[PDB]
Length: 59
Length: 59
Figure 1 (cartoon, rainbow over the protein chains, first blue to last red):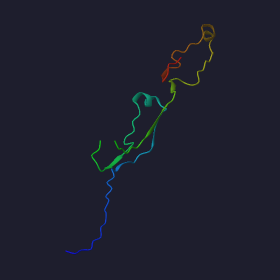
Figure 2: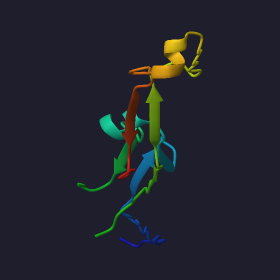
Figure 3: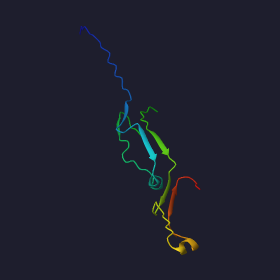
Figure 4: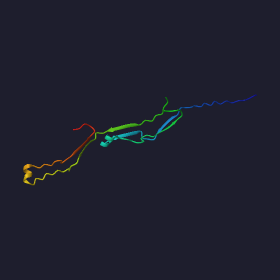
């Protein structure tokens, strides 16, 4: 079987892409200016929202 | 251990809250009209009632 062939080399580069995005401010500020602020403490709800994308199993 | 990290900076502002409240009239008036007021003197009990709150040890 006489042939004429042309070869291409396919190089798949599987990079380990881990991508953690956040939807909150970089700086979270606690300003204790009132007595009730000291006594009961300061709570900030949902300060950061982490969205996750990952190729591999992650912790 | 390949990672992808997002950092938040927490800045706690510990302010020196000193809170002195009073439950009396700002103006305390002594009206010496009768002779007995001059001789025995004028006394007002419970003129002011100081309530105290403070972050730090106080005097």
